[PDB]
Length: 8
Length: 243
Ligand SMILES: CC1(C)CCC[C@](C)([C@H]2CC[C@]3(C)[C@@H]2[C@H](O)C[C@@H]2[C@@]4(C)CC[C@H](O)C(C)(C)[C@@H]4CC[C@]23C)O1
Image 1 (spheres, rainbow over the protein chains, first blue to last red):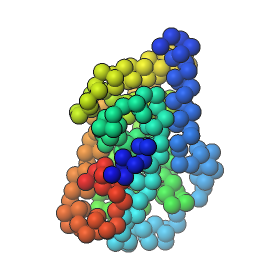
Image 2 (spheres, each protein chain N blue to C red):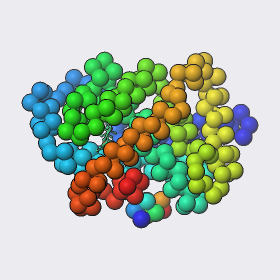
Image 3 (tube, rainbow over the protein chains, first blue to last red):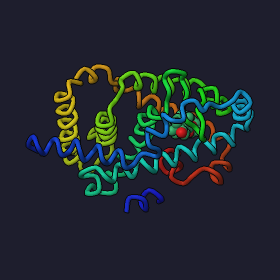
C-alpha cells in the first residue's frame, strides 16, 4: 500500500 | 496534561498545521484578483468528464498527502498501530481537506484558487456532481464566516482526525486520551482568547460526514461507468482511501 509507505 | 503543558500542545499543533499546508495563506490572498476568464471557465466546462475527474483527483490526492504529513506530526499518531493510523486517515483525511479548503476560498465572490487562478463552482461543471460541489462551496462559505485564526483551524482539523469514535480502532482508549488532550487544548485556547462563541457555530456533526459520503457514492457511479480510467489514471493513494 502507498499509505503504508507514506506512514514511514 | 497541566496548564503550561496544555498550551505547549496548542503551540505544537499550530506549528504542525502551518508546516503542512500546500500554499502559504499570504500567497493565496495576494492572488485574489487573478480570476479565470469566461473563456478559461468554458474550457474547463467543456473538458471531458473523465479527464476533469482525473485532474481533480490528482489535486485532491496532493492535498491528502499534506494531510498525511500533518497527521504524522500530531502527538501520539506515529505511536498508534498502522491499522489505527489508517482507520483515522480513511475516516478523516478528506474531511480535513474540506476544512483546509476555506484558506483557498474567497467568500466575497464565492471563488476558490484552482490551478493558478480563482474560479467559481461553475468551473467544475464537467464533473457531473453539481449538487455536491455546491454543498462543498457552501460549507467553505460557512467556515469563512467564522474567521478562524491559524490556531483555531489547526486545532479544529486535528480534532477532525483524532476521533476515538471511528469504527475499527484497535486502541480506542489511547485515541480517547489523544482526543481529550486536543479538546482541552482547543477549549483552553478559545477561553483564553475570548473565542468560545465559535463552538456553537462550528458545523454540525454529520455535515462533513455527509459530504464525504456523497463523494464516495458519486465515485461508485464513476468507477462503474469508467473502470479502466480509474485503474489507469487515478492515483493509488486516492484509490486506497476511497474505492
Ligand atoms: C473526486 C472528484 C473528482 C469528484 C467528486 C467531487 C470532488 C471531490 C471535488 C469536490 C471539491 C473539490 C472540487 C474536489 C476536487 O477533487 C478537488 C478540490 C481541491 C482540493 C482541488 C485543488 C484546489 O486548489 C482546492 C481549492 C484545494 C480544491 C477544493 C475543492 C476540491 C476538494 O472531486
